[PDB]
């Protein structure tokens, strides 16, 4: 949890322009959040990147979790190993608003973060899930009460989020 180079947005939300895979390798946090889907199939975006950085160990573990427990619900989560990236991976499902899933569930998704004192995380429902990323940061600020270190890869998006928030 020895994070460095973050900008403090609120009492408990920090942001950095960084690849979440590189941040996890440098800090080895207690918890890294994955932007997952209900079957834990890590095909692209942040999920694909975290799974590739584990050389597919995360996907084999996720498949066994699904065969034993069934899929997650939208807004839900599960805790699995963080492999070489973290002690634990918190897999969280934000709504895919491009598929008609309710934006109301983005608040439920971020509520999962409150079970952990410190997290390294991406914005939820951004990218292929279709939510506006600045809206997703606002829900994060309004819902998360524990200490969250947000990593945003794209510099253009990062600059827009810092300008809209500060
Ligand atoms: N080594 C890697 O491949 N790392 C990463 N691959 C992605 C892919 C998508 C993203 C996304 C966003 C971003 O933070 O720029 C907002 C939407 C999806 C972030 C990473 S970090």
Image: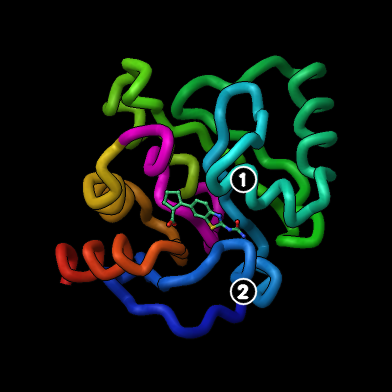
Colour pattern? rainbow
Examine the rendered structure and indicate whether residue 143 appears above or below residue 6. Answer: above
Which residue is under mark 1? 90
Closer to us: 60 or 75: 60
Q: Give the Cα separation between the discs numbered 2 and 1.
A: 15 Å
Q: Earlier in the sequence, mark 2 or mark 1?
A: 2
Other-residue count near label 2 (Cα within 10 Å), few / some / many at <14 / 14–19 / ≥20: some
Q: Quadrant of residue 16?
A: bottom left
- Relative to 77, say whether 22 is above or below: below
Q: Quadrant of the C terminus?
A: bottom left
Quadrant into which the N terminus falls:
bottom right
Relative depth, front residue between 103 and 54: 54
Q: Is residue 92 magenta?
A: no
| Residue 91 image offset from top left, x and y in percent | 60, 40
Graded by Cα atoms within 10 Å as few (under 14), some (14 to 19) or many (20 or more), the crowding at tag 1 reads many
Task: Provide the secondary structure element on which disc 2 rests.
Answer: loop
Asked whether 134 or 128 is in front, the reply is 128
Region in magenta: 114-130
Indicate yes or no whether the magenta region holds residue 116: yes
**Residue closer to the observer: 29 or 99:** 99
What residue is pinned by disc 2?
A: 1
Residue at coordinates 56% horizontally, 29% vertically from top-left? Answer: 37
Q: Along the horizontal axis of the image, is 159 left or right of 101?
A: left
* Left or right of residue 140, residue 22 in this image: right
């Amino acid at each position: 949890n020895s994070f460095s180079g973050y900008l403090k947005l609120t009492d408990n939300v920090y942001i950095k322009n960084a690849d979440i895979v590189e941040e996890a390798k440098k800090v080895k946090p207690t918890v890294v959040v994955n932007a997952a889907n209900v079957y834990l199939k890590h095909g692209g975006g942040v999920a694909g990147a975290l799974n590739k950085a584990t050389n597919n160990a995360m996907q084999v573990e996720s498949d066994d979790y699904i065969a034993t427990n069934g899929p997650l619900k939208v807004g839900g989560s599960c805790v699995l190993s963080g492999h070489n990236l973290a002690k634990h991976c918190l897999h969280v499902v934000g709504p895919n608003v491009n598929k008609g899933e309710d934006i109301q569930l983005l608040k439920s998704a971020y509520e999962n973060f409150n079970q952990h004192e410190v997290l390294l995380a991406p914005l939820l429902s951004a990218g292929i899930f279709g939510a506006d990323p600045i809206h997703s940061l606002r829900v994060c600020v309004d819902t998360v009460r524990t200490n969250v270190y947000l990593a945003v890869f794209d510099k253009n998006l990062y600059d827009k989020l810092v300008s809209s928030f500060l």
